[PDB]
Amino acid sequence: HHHHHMSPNLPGQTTVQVRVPYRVVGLVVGPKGATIKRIQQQTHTYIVTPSRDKEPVFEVTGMPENVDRAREEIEMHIAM
Image (cartoon, rainbow, N blue to C red; front, side, top):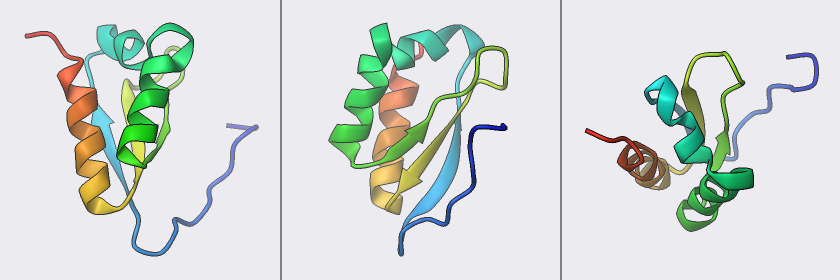
């Protein structure tokens, strides 16, 4: 993207990919991004939301234990 850049993570932090069904990206983001903002604050992670018509993949950055916690909150927003 012309308006984004790659930055190295803080020491000890990793970045993983969390794939969701395309229909539930809006559920994870929530109204005005309140849901995805709550996940970042509660899990102490940095999460990039995928674009409009791109791969429904969230990029979660943080400590490995915190990144795993953020992955579960994202995957819980998926109906069976």
